[PDB]
Image 1 (spheres, each protein chain N blue to C red):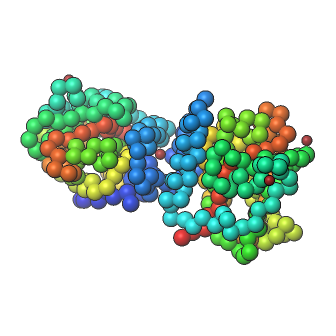
Image 2 (cartoon, rainbow over the protein chains, first blue to last red):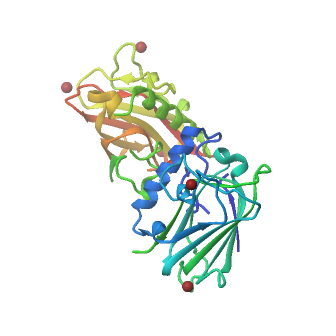
Length: 188
Length: 180
Ligand SMILES: [Br-]
Ligand SMILES: [Br-]
Ligand SMILES: [Br-]
Ligand SMILES: [Br-]
Ligand SMILES: [Br-]
Ligand SMILES: [Br-]
């Protein structure tokens, strides 16, 4: 029900080496892992369904739309603009068999905009979504892949049409949050 | 027993083989990759036993000794000076548990001095050494971390051929590690 994320579980971190690669990541190292992570995920068999869903942010600062978390750029990010918790709604036109939800987290690059807790909800609709997991982002710099190995009933998959992400608190007294990249995949 | 090294083929399965990631980079970039790969490797759960072994090359040009492949410096390199195959013998005072052998390859920087095939042997000594792996350096610019761990006291690398009609070979960096 709760996943502690502290890259200092293996398959969870798309980046890293054998574990953290850089004890003190630089803008260059961060950008590198971002881009490498995208290459690695896309090399997998699964299909990228990210841009097939409708993405609705609770709020956003003008010039930092939600599309900036869906592109393939390390330098761009969606930035909320409101009170907490911030929210992100994902709605597909039909039910989906999500095998992987990947999220780029960087406490070094985002500082106060880096979320420290993330709550994931999925279902048929907002009035139906059910709590799935709590991500405790304690120390992370890179791509994390959620495989839903839980509930082997649906056999490692997140069958849903709607997904909700809640951001109730950030690192370092941050009010608003940043999201540079997130991706959703289905099998085959 | 044949490892085809090509850092252009993205594959989750080989991400830890290519220390500097998947793929002309400038000399500054190459330089950065070299020192970054060293930081990545040293910051790992491993013990660097490189300088504990005795290193003996089949030949070397004066001014480009074997020490230049073990100095953690990108601009320096061991350079052979003889007919092929070139050879590098590594001998420890005792049986080691090598979990990783890291080698820096750069076809861009080394051009004709870049090996296209490397044959790796290991054992107790030159007399009992056994063939372990054939490295096919097809396209590499960065550090390669070979996981084979492998308990041996003696390691031998043979360089039978280089890219682009090259007679002699360059090695800017190589390091050995045992589990922590
Ligand atoms: Br990486
Ligand atoms: Br906008
Ligand atoms: Br559903
Ligand atoms: Br010399
Ligand atoms: Br010759
Ligand atoms: Br032995």
